[PDB]
Length: 228
Image 1: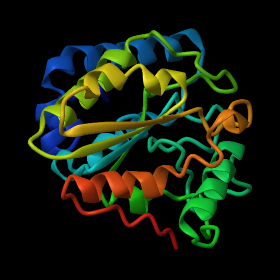
Image 2: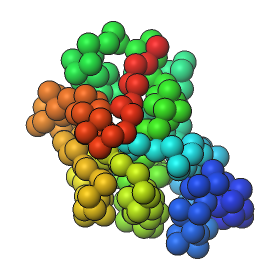
Image 3: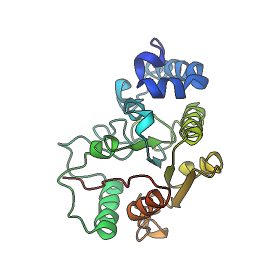
Image 4: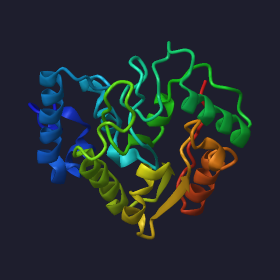
């Protein structure tokens, strides 16, 4: 549908204005995914979930979390970075690692399920640097045109007259650091929660509590991170 329908239809009003400079690029990504299907290759998440992160209000974002690309296993990715549908179990190992750090950092019990929508509904943008992947092949759509879209999104948030905290998980997420240089923006960076990288600095990084300290310091309301 992103080949065929305008941003005014695909995403929330604030996001449609914020992504105007990449309107043509988004249509192009629509044609890229159409070509993958034509060729008999698959993508995740489902087409109608690809831009889901931009369907919550642009004006309400206080924190963004940025990962690499969507979950590679069919049935996991839903268009919100690291989120899974409420009926998914077991949790993907990166999300089990996030929830371990979440309990260590904040003292809360393990969430009931893998659904991060409460965060999306409380001013957290759940972004992946790249918004599609081929099943079972991490980073398979790196450098196919999404990066200009996620760069435009971060630049737009940063230009708002509002505080912003960015939590940047892993190397592809960290390439947005330069666009956050302005005085109303602060970036937290750590290795990715994936089992391959988590032991190099994700565990003990306290991203949730540090994000709230940074917000309070800038005169913003902290995120209520508590999942049911």
